[PDB]
Image (cartoon, rainbow over all chains, first blue to last red; front, side):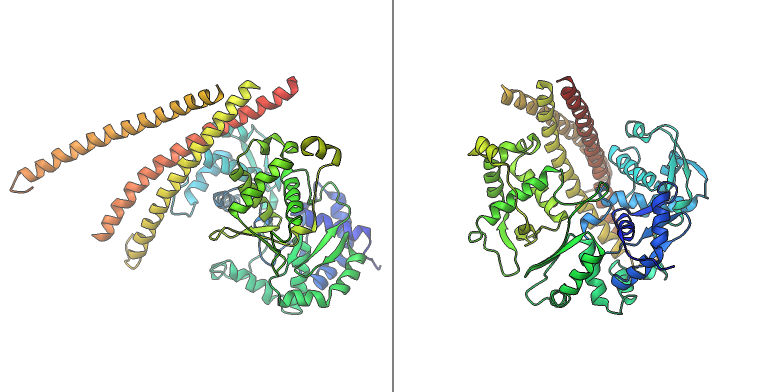
Length: 384
Length: 49
Length: 49
Length: 49
């Protein structure tokens, strides 16, 4: 029996990546298919990434541990740190519940309030706190960590006395990867990386590069003399051959950035551009920046530098040209609000960073990879 | 549409008011955070709740 | 007309704010007077300002 | 004594901060209720069109 990396292996890998984990009870076909190549995949993951993958009877999960965590990676449905704190408290609660045990939502709120380890108390009488817990519960239910049929927490939104009957599912035990030491010894999150890389000392650079490339849409050059980027240059070519054999991607390399493009995204895949209009306006901004390279001098790092004021002028100028075709949502929003949202969005896709203090805008060359415009007949109808 | 525009503008107004109120709340929170930091820190050494 | 409506709403908001502020002002003054009488009571027993 | 002074400041700020937190949450409730109401009404308006 000798399996080979084919369409099926690519599909299993993609399914693993674009989901947090795969549950047997709902994706039995994918689970079996993945299981069939699981042998080749484990070897391959070790060879290229060095990442571990644990496949067991009820689910399969790929510990997509990033080289350096980024904001967009996290559960996006969550909006405050408090949401994560409540999530962790919910986890502790599930640690308190036996498998297939049934508990009421009211009990969960009470124990979470009691246990909550922060100095500043959590109060369930507020609306915002209840919204945070409901979002946490929704994410919990998404992974079937907890099942739910009686009522609907949404009424809990406008009725804190609302009640629902929940059942603790088996998956709660296995949800979180393992932390082999005294977890308290991990006095700070940075110490976790020192673990994952004490486990990846052998050819650490290649595994680092593979993780950085595969996770992020792109990999930005730290500076003119970045050792990592020189490394990338030395094995750009062998990477390209491997990538053509093994995946959907097509490699691109430039002086200050390197990235993977994808040719055919499926339903379940995430890609840029997408439907959200802000990508469109980001592209329009990209074209506008491309059109004045000298005024917005790309610096040696491939970045383009603009101050918040300069950016606001650009956004006004853009609203003048393409604003006619924008959604009424943005057309109706002040310059500064659009500025804040677009800059957060561009951070999520790593196109740029806004220095908090000096307000300098750094636009990465990856932003300059793509530019967009409306069809010409409308551009002339809108603003000729 | 008229009701929608009126409620949207009113909602935007309340958005401003809420933002300023949350600003004030976080200002007070910063003061309180500094005070709690100092109090627990300076009373840290003592074997006292 | 839109601006007139908006500013009327603004007026309702500012009036609410002013009323709440005056409420807190009255409450604070009442508590201040209670504290003042208690202070006077506890100083009256002997020679203090 | 100094830590007691810090404690009085913290308690004062804690009650004010709780007041502000409840006020801000109430305004958030108001804003979100209006936003949900406006969005359902907006879909209703598209459907009606």
